[PDB]
Amino acid sequence: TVQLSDQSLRQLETLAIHTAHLIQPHGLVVVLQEPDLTISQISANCTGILGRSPEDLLGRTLGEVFDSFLTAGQISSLNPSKLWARVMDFVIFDGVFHRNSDGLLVCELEPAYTSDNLPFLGFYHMANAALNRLNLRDFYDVIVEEVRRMTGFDRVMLYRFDENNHGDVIAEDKRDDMEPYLGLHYPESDIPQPARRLFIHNPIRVIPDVYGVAVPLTPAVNPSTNRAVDLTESILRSAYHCHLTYLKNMGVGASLTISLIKDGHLWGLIACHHQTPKVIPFELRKACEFFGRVVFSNISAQEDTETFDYRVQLAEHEAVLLDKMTTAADFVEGLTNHPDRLLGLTGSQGAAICFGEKLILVGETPDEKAVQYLLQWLENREVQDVFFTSSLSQIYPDAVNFKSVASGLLAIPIARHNFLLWFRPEVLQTVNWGGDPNHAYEATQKIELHPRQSFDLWKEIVRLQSLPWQSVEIQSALALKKAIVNLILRQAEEHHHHHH
Amino acid sequence: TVQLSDQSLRQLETLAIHTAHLIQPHGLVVVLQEPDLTISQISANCTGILGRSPEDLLGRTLGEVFDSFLTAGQISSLNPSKLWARVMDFVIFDGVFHRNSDGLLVCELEPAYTSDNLPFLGFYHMANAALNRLNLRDFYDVIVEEVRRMTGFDRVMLYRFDENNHGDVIAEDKRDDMEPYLGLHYPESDIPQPARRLFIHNPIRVIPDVYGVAVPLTPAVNPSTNRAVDLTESILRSAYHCHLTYLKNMGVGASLTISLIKDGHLWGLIACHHQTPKVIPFELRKACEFFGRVVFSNISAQEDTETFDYRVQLAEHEAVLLDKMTTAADFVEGLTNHPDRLLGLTGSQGAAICFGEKLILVGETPDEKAVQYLLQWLENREVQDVFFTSSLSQIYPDAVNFKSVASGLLAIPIARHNFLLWFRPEVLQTVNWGGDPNHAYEATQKIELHPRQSFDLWKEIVRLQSLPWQSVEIQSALALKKAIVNLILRQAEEHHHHHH
Ligand SMILES: *[C@H](C)[C@H]1/C(=C/c2[nH]c(/C=C3N=C(/C=C4\NC(=O)C(CC)=C4C)C(C)=C\3CCC(=O)O)c(CCC(=O)O)c2C)NC(=O)[C@@H]1C
Ligand SMILES: *[C@H](C)[C@H]1/C(=C/c2[nH]c(/C=C3N=C(/C=C4\NC(=O)C(CC)=C4C)C(C)=C\3CCC(=O)O)c(CCC(=O)O)c2C)NC(=O)[C@@H]1C
């Protein structure tokens, strides 16, 4: 169980979903050798929809298997383009070209339905009206609602990954008869690393039919490159079976997933579900993204500005401390006479200054002997860099007896034996999981992972834990350490004299 | 002259400013072998400031040449750190570590002045107040003013690269006695490609003394890697001499340059100049960037939203056309009865529909025979993709006689012989250059480039040229072509029947 859990986690992080050679059944995939546009490989479903199989096809080229009206960046202008064939029966595709990271042309023919197109005044009309009409919550809700408006989906949500790559549904529009996922929290193993890295490279993933059986590329390997073909940028690649199994027991027949990138990292996803299978054409997908992205630009801007705002809060405290410190006598005197500021510097409720032989406690701290034993623990463990923890109990067992006052500890050293300590109380935090995280998935045994069946609200109460240490707060704490080091250095050179 | 101009341009794009091995004189550079932190190479200026040269130093390690209070991502926590040495004389540095793209540790010791620090309430106090107190112009001016406030610089500007990588000073704060550069336009050769690619990787470049003579790394090559060391991420690397020569005749003794990135491309620069040499410490630099970046996040958001807004303008036109087209008889009938919409679709003043045997002109066009000869020119040149030009004169010489009505031409083909054309009139555009662009630089001859001496306003009048074709307008034009192709395809399958 514990061992099975362990390597099953290691199996998730390493999955090769991109080197899988199976395509969704509704559309055709071909990989083109050139200059010529010869068909080296093709999906097996061509038999059922074209009529000419990997007998008649393969190396007969795109030229005249299809009709229409090795290149380079011209692919962009070709995306999408109408390709059609007559086989007695008239099929019309919208083809989308791309080149792999390996550097070979894949063409993905989706059945085109749009001979007649669009809602009133385009896919954008209503959505733009809402965006202009203007807080972060407003942005969150506009995405999911106006995307659900454009699309016709049973459920549309905004899924935001946290610092541990878990995720939360932070916004949702849905039919009123469906049970809400708003505010549910999900394990990181649901969207494992290989799936997340895909969304840095592939901004859209659509699955019009979950129950559709994936057909294999023939041959499974590329004849030229001597490898499986990388379908990371692939529209028609079939999602890993486990994820399909995951969507089935959640009750989803179709999905559209658009990823949101901040500063080149996966911030989150616009996640769309349908109970029934559904056609989401290319132009619609591309529309939902362009909108999603514009609002996200504004989301990114806001959270950036809120981040800068908190940084200046802590910057005021620092300055007040740096001013009162230098100008007063012992720097320790300056720090202690302004508790409010010392505590605010890192968003904490208590602190301790251990310098030379004097030990000063400020605010809500553990009692002196307790902090003094902690300081010895800090010394015994040879802390040189910078130490913080949101749950001191679980690394310092004795800390359980003052978890009320110091479940959190930020500890910064100032040379040998000297420390600055900030303390934080236990704050009970309730997490609302989408299902029991103790069985986030299940492994059978030859390791075989299977997704969980229930996703019903499962309330956790997190204990023996403070608020988490934000990075701006730790940097602030080091800004003080550096200002203190500045003063020791100022003294040092005040006692230095030149030459003779 | 013309040949000299040509290869001198080719020399600029290929310069290896990053593989130069010369460092600025005020600070020390060392490259550390490890595990050990041995000094493999070091700047020659150590003699003049440490007292121990590449005799006493080299392989004596950072350990005890310096005092303080091969790693990995711990470099971040070490940046910056106080390093000091006593050599009878007490020097105090602020060291900043980084690892190359080649993967080796470079340590850059800047003389530390800040034993006593900061303005009131930190480097941010005033700047944050302005940002919250809230259009793009507002953002532009807040950057340059509040940066000039924080810094004490003689001139601070916002430099924005255009589509051709030329640039414009779009915002500026300066002493009132200095001649303004606001609104001046500069050649792309001033910030050549190698300099631009540097700012994707290195967000800050500071030169506290332009006149300071660069000292060489000894040895010039790294002994382990067998190459010159890549100083792209280097603080203390000396800017290429030509750029220093460029700053001298502009009258700049010191500069600080912070780059602004949108969606992973170089949008622009916060460019700071001082007439006199100036010390800009690390913490100040890092402050100016963090602020600059926060406001830029809001800039990026705004221009993104203005981009989306124009896209919806054109999206309305398209929809109106797609609606009136299909439902009416000949699609050409629908398009022609709504000239306003057809012209607005691509922001143009006239158009022509050439389909089958009928040729319809709309709005301000060249006369029929002229457009008909143009259509033959379009046919004779075998246009298959999509053709546009902001100056039709210079590719179609005869177009000079109707430059008043069609200096600009967007031309989209709909299968064989059929075209959609949009026309745009000559609009006189005046460019205000910072100096005569005809002598943007000068080459002597063994090619030796030298920067220009004058940067005084040089007014250009651009002729025979329309407004430039934006990408949203071209895509819009193709959205119509695709909707027309949809209708031909709809007919095609309306005449198709199944089986027997
Ligand atoms: C299989 C045993 C394990 C597993 C693997 C896995 N997951 C994915 C992909 C996704 N998971 C999500 C998750 C959600 N979307 C939601 O709307 C919600 C809550 C309502 C959740 C939790 C998403 C969005 C994706 C990808 C986007 C998409 O729809 O495709 C993959 C992807 C594989 C691929 O080939 O693309 C894999 C292999 N998931 C599990 O739960 C098991 C632990
Ligand atoms: C030399 C013959 C050619 C040349 C080379 C060159 N330029 C640069 C770097 C920069 N150029 C700019 C330009 C401006 N900054 C401004 O404020 C203004 C107007 C007021 C201009 C035009 C900038 C900002 C930089 C870099 C930033 C910095 O300050 O360092 C390089 C860089 C080399 C390096 O090693 O970093 C080189 C080689 N410039 C010319 O004009 C000649 C054509």
Image: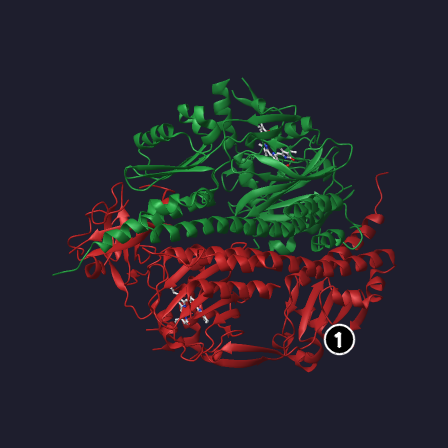
Chain colours: A green, B red
Which residue shows up at 76% across the image and 55% down it? B483
Which chain contains the residue that carries disc 1? B
Which residue shows up at 69% across the image and 50% down it? A287
Q: Position of residue B265 (x, y in %)?
A: 51, 57
Quadrant of res B2: bottom left
> Which of the pair A213/A16 is nearer the observer?
A16
Which residue shows up at 44% across the image and 27% down it? A402
- The answer, for residue B461, to whether it is visible in the render is yes
Element type at mark 1:
loop
* Quadrant showing the C terminus of chain B: top right
> Which of the pair B203/A372 is nearer the observer?
A372
Is A94 left or right of B137, judged from the image as shown?
right
Q: Position of residue B125 (x, y in %)?
A: 48, 57
> Which of the pair B286/A46 is nearer the observer?
B286
Is B65 left or right of A33, judged from the image as shown?
left
Up the image or down, B213 lies above or below B80; here it is below
Residue that label 1 marks: B365
